Image (cartoon, rainbow over all chains, first blue to last red; front, side, top):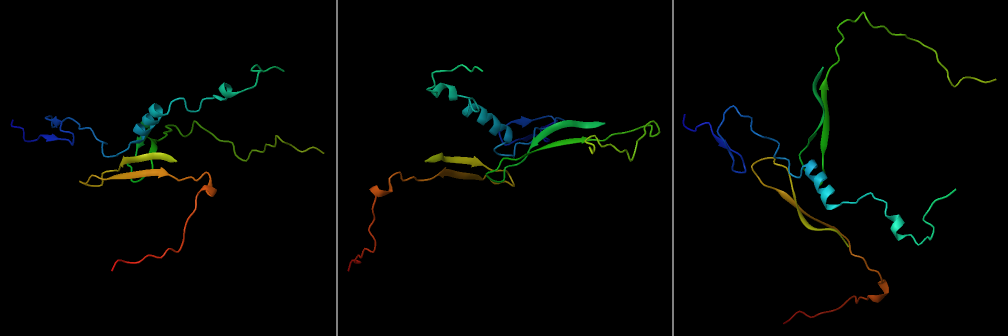
Length: 64
Length: 51
Length: 48
């Protein structure tokens, strides 16, 4: 019938199906997954061994 | 019997701290309790005594 | 030395209120303490 059992979320999207499960879990600002993705993007090459590129040692080969 | 496998669900941010938790729901079921057995009061000293 | 500039961090939703934090991490450093000086106990007159 008429759109009486209709609702919208905080972002302006409307759901017209009373039996459709609405998405949830949007109230946790600064989500941990977002923080992990941000760390992966803004800080690449973290934990890499670059000590070899500033070594003045003429011998770069390890032998017994 | 698994209600859900091991998974992480993120918590709310109430300060300058990032929090999350890991959950698992289940229970072990043994249909025949008389088809198992246990040994009790076993003695074992692998790092034994010398002398 | 700044660990991070002025920034905005979102908080949780405990009700129909929008709330966030503003943070900055840092510390001043003086490399040569002998190149500064200060005066102490200076007297001044209020205008009359």
